[PDB]
Amino acid sequence: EIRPTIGQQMETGDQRFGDLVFRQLAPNVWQHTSYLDMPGFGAVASNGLIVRDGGRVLVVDTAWTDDQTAQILNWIKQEINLPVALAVVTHAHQDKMGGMDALHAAGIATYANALSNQLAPQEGMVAAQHSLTFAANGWVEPATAPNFGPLKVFYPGPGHTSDNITVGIDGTDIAFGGCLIKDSKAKSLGNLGDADTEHYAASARAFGAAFPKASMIVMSHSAPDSRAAITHTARMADKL
Ligand SMILES: [O-]
Ligand SMILES: [Zn+2]
Ligand SMILES: [Zn+2]
Image 1: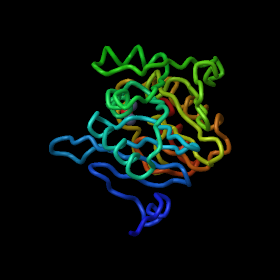
Image 2 (image 1 turned 90 degrees about the horizontal axis):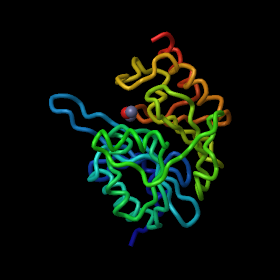
Image 3 (image 1 turned 180 degrees about the horizontal axis):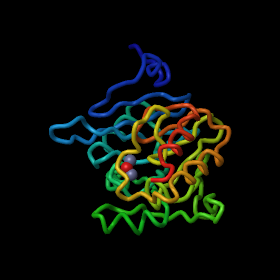
Image 4 (image 1 turned 120 degrees about the horizontal axis):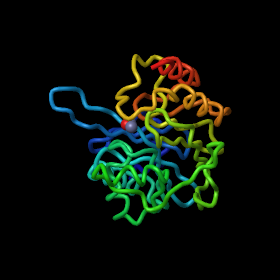
């Protein structure tokens, strides 16, 4: 008989759900966190977003696996119970696109950088259903991003990967750097095996310039931070 809203519940603090963690960042915006078990070592965390936009939900990034992504969808059903209209996934690595099959089975329309949709299938991953094309200035061509609501998608240039994209949430102070940006105390940029080391620093800067009003920077592999994360990341990336 105690029936708080999800917002009221998330005041208590971050919530464990199955093998995931959820955190409310602002009303109508939650961070999902999933973990890749690496035998003998600590599990690798990855963050994405869930946005309630009127009577629908929008997702940024899958979890590492289909099952973890199904757990995200279970949380949305239990706590929000609105249809998930679409998902945007932010490059062709496992932490961002490892759960595409779960999204597709749920009837969710999926979008990724056209380049991610080329890169993913040859890695044994599944492409998104729709491809985003970006103008030379980095902004998504609106015709390729129909019905995105508050999501503003920006290609900052090659960095963490050649295909990495970023997402601002209009009406909030939040911008999602995905795996491009690490927090202002990070001692490394993580696995740079697919990175463009020449352009990384400039791409981090371009993300900051694209979303100048975003005071909360959300990231895949760090907890949310203030804007100092952006220049810290660019400093770490300088002259790799
Ligand atoms: O990643
Ligand atoms: Zn990555
Ligand atoms: Zn990542």
